[PDB]
Image: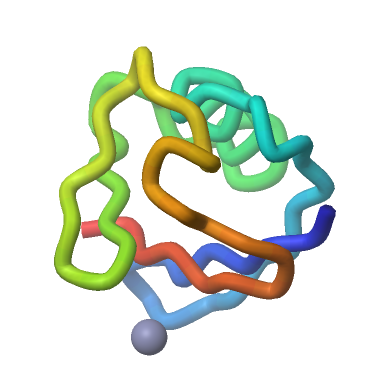
Length: 70
Ligand SMILES: [Zn+2]
């Protein structure tokens, strides 16, 4: 499925992920795309802070959703 991530500069990157991907997996993909170290990445979705060991489905993140780096 496709989701979008907004960086701290407002840039929007697209990611191909699976419903079961963990936040840790997503952070690794962001690192490959932008070079931002995982440990300095904090992701938010609908006002919810996302934990590394949980999956996208755990947060009801569906196709075309947008996450924010803060
Ligand atoms: Zn938004």
